[PDB]
Image (cartoon, coloured by chain):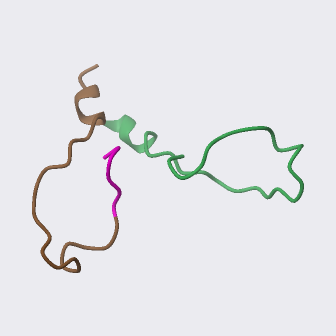
Chain colours: A brown, B green
Amino acid sequence: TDNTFVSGNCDVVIGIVNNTVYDPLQPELDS
Amino acid sequence: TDNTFVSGNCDVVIGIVNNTVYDPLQPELDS
């Protein structure tokens, strides 16, 4: 998330690919 | 907070207006 930002929708971009965006806040929930 | 940076105070800048700054870490506290 730190290297990317959210814009538009997946049905807009032509040629978009699916993947998992790492969220540094998820592993911090264990602390 | 990602699109702005906190500096100075509210009594210096001329023409400052009041508003609310959304914090993405506030709603994540429930998890």
Q: Is residue B12 left or right of residue A21?
A: right
Measuring 10% from the left and 65% from the top, which residue is drawn there? A17
In this rendering, the answer to whether A9 lies above or below A28 is below
For residue A5: magenta? yes
Is residue B23 highlighted in magenta?
no
Q: Quadrant of the C terminus of chain A?
A: top left
Q: Report how many numbered discs are placed on residues in the image.
A: 0
Residue drawn at x 35%, y 57% is A5
- Prevalent SS, magenta region: loop
Q: Position of residue B30 (x, y in %)?
A: 35, 37
**Foreground residue, B22 or B14?**
B14
Q: Is residue A23 left or right of residue B20?
A: left
Q: Is residue A4 above or below residue A29?
A: below
Quarter-wise, where is residue A22 in the image? top left
Left or right of residue B9, residue A2 in this image: left
From the top left corner, tell me how far across and down residue A15 is, in percent.
12, 75
Q: Name the residue rendered at 22%, 77% in the picture.
A: A13
Q: Give percent across and percent down for residue B7.
A: 72, 38
Point out the residue furthest to the top here: A31
Residue visible at 11% across and 55% down in the picture: A19
Q: Is residue A1 above or below residue A10?
A: above
Residue B29 in which image quadrant: top left
Residue closer to the observer: B11 or A19: A19
Tell me where the magenta segment starts and ends, as one range: A1-6
